[PDB]
Structures are given as C-alpha cells and as structure tokens.
Amino acid sequence: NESDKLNEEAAKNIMVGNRCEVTVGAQMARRGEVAYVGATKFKEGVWVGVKYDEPVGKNDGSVAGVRYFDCDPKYGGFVRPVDVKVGDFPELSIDEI
C-alpha cells in the first residue's frame, strides 16, 4: 500500500530521455538514461527501464521475450521508481586528467 504510493509519487517526474542514477538496495549507484516508464507484463505497478552507461544491467531491453526498449545485452535494467533519481547525471568517465 505505502510502497505503491511512494512509487507513483516518484514516477511523476520521471520522463523517458532523462539522465538518471539507479540505486538498488546495497548496490553501487549506476548512471544511464530512462528508456521506459510505466506498466509492464512481468509484474504489477510502475517500472522504470534504464539504458545504462556501462554493461551493468540484466537485460537487452526485453524481459520474458517482450521488448520494451532497445539496447545492447546487459545494458538494460528495470527497477522501481523509488530506486531512480532523474536529473543532471552525466556519464562517470575520465578521458584524461
């Protein structure tokens, strides 16, 4: 009950194309771009599909044979809106310093 409310609230400002940072549980934060926001076929509620900067995801934009977005293998992930912050989150990389 409380979780659905928290997820619905967090999703209101999450738009496809937004840069983002994903923090799932204990894991290291990972940045990418929002590729999907809304309901899916695999579980009820709101999901955020992310196209990650590094191959640190779990999918290729598809889950259970259903395509939701396009990306390379291991660059995609689906997480709950509460685990996603959107804003100016540029790619963590240093060319030369």
Image (cartoon, helix red, strand yellow):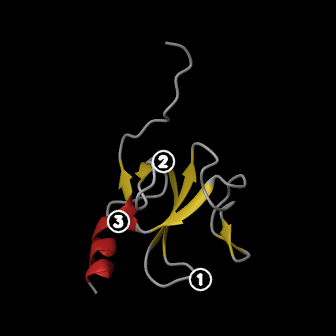
Q: Secondary structure at mark 2?
A: strand
Look at the picture and state if 25 lies above or below 94: below
Q: Which residue is the site of mark 1?
A: 41
Mark toward the start of the polypeptide (1 vs 3): 1
Between residue 47 and residue 38, name the one nearer to us. Answer: 47
Between residue 67 and residue 79, name the one nearer to us. Answer: 79
Percent x, y of residue 39: 50, 78
Q: Which residue is the site of mark 3?
A: 82
Direction front: furthest residue = 26
Indicate the amino acid at tag 1.
Answer: Lys
Mark toward the start of the polypeptide (1 vs 2): 2
Q: Quadrant of the N terminus?
A: bottom left
Residue drawn at (33%, 80%) of the image: 4
Look at the picture and state if 40 lies above or below 83: below
Q: Which mark is residue 30?
A: 2
Q: Secondary structure at mark 1?
A: loop
Residue drawn at (49%, 12%) of the image: 97
Image marks 3 and 2: residues in contact by CB distance under 8 Å: no
Residue drawn at (48%, 47%) of the image: 30
- Separation of disc 1 and disc 2 at Cα? 25 Å
Look at the picture and state if 55 lies above or below 43: above
Percent x, y of residue 21: 42, 49
Q: Which mark is residue 5?
A: none
Indicate the amino acid at tag 2.
Answer: Arg
Q: Residues within 10 Å of mark 3 (few under 14, many from 20)?
A: many
- Separation of disc 3 and disc 2 at Cα? 14 Å
Q: Secondary structure at mark 3?
A: helix
Indicate the amino acid at tag 3.
Answer: Val
- Separation of disc 1 and disc 3 at Cα? 19 Å
